[PDB]
Image (cartoon, coloured by chain):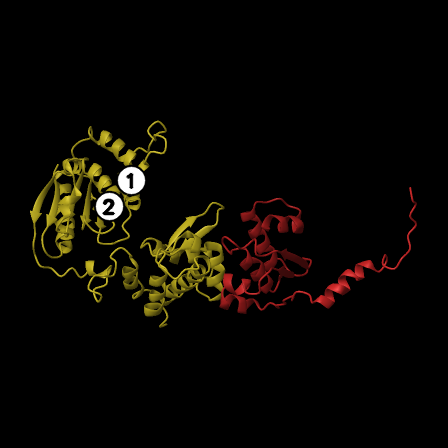
Amino acid sequence: CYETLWNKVSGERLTWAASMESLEFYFKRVPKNKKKTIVVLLDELDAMVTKSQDIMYNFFNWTTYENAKLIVIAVANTMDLPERQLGNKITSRIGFTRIMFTGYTHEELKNIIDLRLKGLNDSFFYVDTK
Amino acid sequence: GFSLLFYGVGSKRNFLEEFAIDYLSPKIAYSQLVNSIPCLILNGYNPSCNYRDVFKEITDLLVPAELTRSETKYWGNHVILQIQKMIDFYKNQPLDIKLILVVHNLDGPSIRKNTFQTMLSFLSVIRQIAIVASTDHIYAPLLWDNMKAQNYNFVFHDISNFEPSTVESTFQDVMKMGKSDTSSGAEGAKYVLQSLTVNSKKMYKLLIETQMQNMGNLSANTGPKRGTQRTGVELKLFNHLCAADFIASNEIALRSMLREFIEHKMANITKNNSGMEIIWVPYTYAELEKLLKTVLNTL
């Protein structure tokens, strides 16, 4: 993820140990007039943090910087994944919002299925019989 | 060419380093005619005494010819195979003592192992280095067979002096009368924290608390598992943790106050299979939370 983020930012192909130093110099040292805001989506954040939890800290700590213009939308499965991996004092220092999506009710499933059938339900087709 | 073992009841430590430093080392140097012989002394009552770090020290003093490719025999042991190259080198050198290795408590907890004794026996064959050793345990001669007693060829001396052993009773808790498991090394770490800098204790407290987060996460187990590389903090993430709490100003001042824990083996630095440089504390989880409360959290 360090390689692919720094490649999308800069167009440069570096190794991962050179990409996180490239990103960390990018977010805290480079001025706000020279950069562009970056909205990165860390999708399925469970899979990145299973072995060493060094990867969830860096993306969240980069957002605490003043010069950084970084919005990490971190979508995962469980709600306690920040507090188990990082700890209590780190997840209070970052100060991120915390949304949970409850699974849909049965009346919400009906307004998904019948919403994808508005152009075809109760409608007329031309079928040839051969 | 005799190695020289001292046994008896009482501490032999103040005897051994007064004989080897004050008497022995100036008088070999005068008899070889300027500087004295280097006297590598070796605290074997320390349960963290590693044989690869001792052999790292000896090759800095002798500077031997390191081991060619035909001599490294398909995952051969480079520590043993370089001593055997060193014996064949020093069988033709002039008979001059140029190192005095002084082993306190040759039957101590980490040094009574078979790989340590095999190192020191083959190293005792070299007549250019003089072994001065000591033993406390009463079944200590059970530790050398006919091959190791040949390479050592000790002459034994009884020095009973009824000394207290107040330095040997530091790596091992005396309030518990000796059931402190003797091989932890964390009780001897408790003594080291008591006289440090407050900025060096705030770092080590931060290192303990962050690894204590990783042991309770990864193990999912109350029982005593001793902390290894998986639970350790990596070094570049640790620099961000101690810059927010104002311990270290940069990477170099962090590495300068880490290495004082590395030389005492209270913290280890090694790299994983990706290049992450992990820093980790070699103690169990129960010894890590006891140490956090008794010396570190009083501020």
Tag in front: 2 or 1: 2
* Label 1: which secondary element: helix
* Label 2: which secondary element: loop
Viewer-side residue, B170 vs B227: B227
Q: Quadrant of the C terminus of chain B?
A: bottom left
Q: Position of residue B254 (x, y in %)?
A: 43, 58
Q: Colour of chain B?
A: yellow
Q: Residue at x 29, y 41 (%)?
A: B60
Q: Residue at x 46, y 54 (%)?
A: B235
Disc assigned to residue B264? none
Crowding at dot 1, Cα within 10 Å, few <14 / some 14-19 / many 20+, comes out as: some
Q: Residue beneath label 2, please? A: B113
Q: Residue beneath label 1, please? A: B59
> Could you say which chain is coloured red in the image?
A
**Which of the marked residues, 2 or 1, is nearer the chain's N terminus?**
1
Residue reaching furthest to the bottom: B298
Q: Quadrant of the N terminus of chain B?
A: top left
Q: Position of residue B33 (x, y in %)?
A: 14, 37
Residue type at numbered disc 2? Lys
Chain where mark 2 sits: B
Q: Position of residue B31 (x, y in %)?
A: 12, 39
Circles 2, 1 touching at the beta carbon (< 8 Å): no
Residue type at numbered disc 1? Thr
Q: Position of residue B264 (x, y in %)?
A: 31, 55
